[PDB]
Amino acid sequence: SDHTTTCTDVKQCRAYLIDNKKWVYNSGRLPRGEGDTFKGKLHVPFVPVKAKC
Amino acid sequence: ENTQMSEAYVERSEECSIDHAKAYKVHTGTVQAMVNITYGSVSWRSADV
Image (tube, rainbow over all chains, first blue to last red):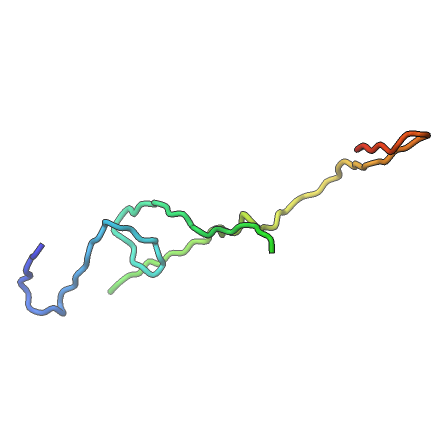
């Protein structure tokens, strides 16, 4: 919370955000997390099935 | 001054359980048939031999 930084410009300091309440699929277009990210699974809804055409 | 990892890895697709090319090796095996038999004054009776 708060933490008023004692420096001058907004262009010389980066910022981040650590939200851990929800979880995301490991895309190839997202940066990898810090350490051990767990292997928790979601089902794939529309699987292949052998039908009649 | 930065570093991006970007590893890649090949695994089996999810449609491989429904169509795939099984690769068999064939040796000689049994021969079966089916016959229709009548004789004299009886009807046709069939069995697997």
